[PDB]
Image (cartoon, coloured by chain):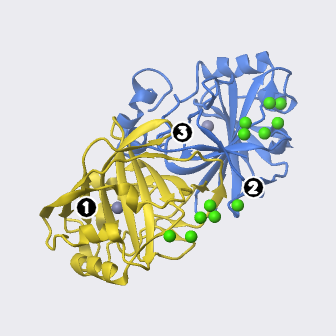
Chain colours: A yellow, B blue
Amino acid sequence: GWSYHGEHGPEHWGDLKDEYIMCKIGKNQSPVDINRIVDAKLKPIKIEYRAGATKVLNNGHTIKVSYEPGSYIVVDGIKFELKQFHFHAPSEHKLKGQHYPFEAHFVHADKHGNLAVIGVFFKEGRENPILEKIWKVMPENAGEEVKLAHKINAEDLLPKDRDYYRYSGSLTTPPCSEGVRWIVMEEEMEMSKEQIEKFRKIMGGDTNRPVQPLNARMIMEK
Amino acid sequence: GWSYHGEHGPEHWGDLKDEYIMCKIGKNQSPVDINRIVDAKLKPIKIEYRAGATKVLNNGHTIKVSYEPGSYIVVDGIKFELKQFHFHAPSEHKLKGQHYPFEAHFVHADKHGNLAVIGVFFKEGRENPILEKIWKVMPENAGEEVKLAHKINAEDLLPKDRDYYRYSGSLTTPPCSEGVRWIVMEEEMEMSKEQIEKFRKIMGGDTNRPVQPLNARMIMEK
Ligand SMILES: [Ca+2]
Ligand SMILES: [Ca+2]
Ligand SMILES: [Ca+2]
Ligand SMILES: [Ca+2]
Ligand SMILES: [Ca+2]
Ligand SMILES: [Ca+2]
Ligand SMILES: [Ca+2]
Ligand SMILES: [Ca+2]
Ligand SMILES: [Ca+2]
Ligand SMILES: [Ca+2]
Ligand SMILES: [Ca+2]
Ligand SMILES: [Ca+2]
Ligand SMILES: [Zn+2]
Ligand SMILES: [Zn+2]
């Protein structure tokens, strides 16, 4: 029942179900305005991806691309397998008070189900050729899914410069579970105005959760 | 009803009351074993304490010293007023898998009630002269409180070297509320074997919560 607008919208999520309690009481929620940063001696994140995108789903909240097993990242010496990537517009995270027009999330899970998410900002620019492959077959209605003709490598959607912001946060959609590793790439990717418009049109509106207070947290920068 | 031992002990806190739900579902709980650390460009914490300790209370869980208003620290540009300090044995936090025999917690709150705690480790060594003033009048039973003859300055219980570990965590006793700034001093203070035994004898046993998983967190070091 949750949505991005109106009476079931983000400010009310925590009243929708008992299972959604973190929305109401969480102190380590995402997304955030990346505005309290410290330089830190972070390790580079090992990204071991293979071409594995298989399906594209419109779930009514985003366009979500499933990934087949075998691609992973390493964070804190632990392997987190890539499950899926999906999109938001405008950006969920803000960077010193400002939005980007689009943000991608690459969702990973370790063997115990702990999650790590890589966030990539997209600005308005040149047409993105990888996205175009997805956009071409993007389902227009909630609940529809389509198989991709050819497997896409999610690594092509990540910047080559891999410096990043890191913090401890949450899922940005209910149940907004905490304990999530957030890795937000410092370098922005690019897509066309037309691509952004198409995504927004299909979604029917904004698909970002409002930024949540950092509270005690600091954001570490590599 | 909560305790450090038995059927109402730390593994069961989250089943005692609905208000203690964080103790069950929290992913940002304290204390922790400080074993995932990264160098960070953190600023010194500004410590503006005045001699202000007025009373000593045995609440059955610890010995807590109240502080009169006017003493504060600055974290993230925000003023957190020192409310009280209290003690645990053995240490709540561990440092690379090892306990210290004793730990002090200096509890601060900002105008909106957000909390910041400074933790200080104590090793067995020389008698601590400031703790001797408190220990001399320490109440032996739960529910007893005594006024100090002379006001103590809590600053004398902090190390002169002010490098620290920082992370986002929780209260270490129910309701174990999150959103707490933890500042754990890297340099240990000292007290006598007899000071440690006397505290432990009055408390009647261990007064530490077990270390909780780091989950998505890193500990930053100044
Ligand atoms: Ca810098
Ligand atoms: Ca950089
Ligand atoms: Ca760069
Ligand atoms: Ca740039
Ligand atoms: Ca770029
Ligand atoms: Ca920077
Ligand atoms: Ca170092
Ligand atoms: Ca030193
Ligand atoms: Ca040092
Ligand atoms: Ca030392
Ligand atoms: Ca020392
Ligand atoms: Ca060190
Ligand atoms: Zn997302
Ligand atoms: Zn404490």
| Residue on which disc 1 sits | A64
Horizontal and vertical percent position of residue A70: 30, 41
Q: Nearer the viewer, mark 1 or mark 3?
A: 1
- Disc 3 crowd, CA 10 A, few/some/many (<14, 14-19, 20+): many
Chain letter behind tag 1 = A
Q: CA distance from mark 1 to mark 3?
A: 35 Å
Q: What is the spatial separation of the Cα atoms under label 1 and label 2, in whole angstroms?
A: 41 Å
- Whether callout 1 and callout 2 share a subunit is answered no
Ligand 2 shown in quarter: bottom right
Q: Secondary structure at mark 3?
A: loop
Q: Is residue B187 above or below residue A116?
A: above
Q: Which residue is mark 3?
A: B30
Which is nearer the eye, A4 or A91? A91
* Chain label for disc 2: B
Query: What amino acid is found at the position of numbered circle 1 in the picture?
Result: Lys
Q: Is residue A19 above or below residue A185?
A: above
- The residue closer to the viewer here, A61 or A86, is A86
